[PDB]
Amino acid sequence: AFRQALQLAACGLAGLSAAVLFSAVAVGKPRAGGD
Image (cartoon, rainbow, N blue to C red):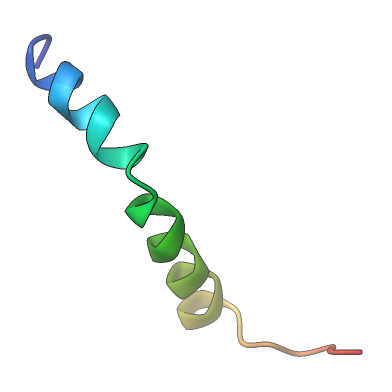
């Protein structure tokens, strides 16, 4: 996992990891309280 951390760390900086969060934020807690 030491050598795999080199490709994994660069795999997240890609910007895709950020798109995954936005999904986990809704599937867990629905948007209740918009303004």
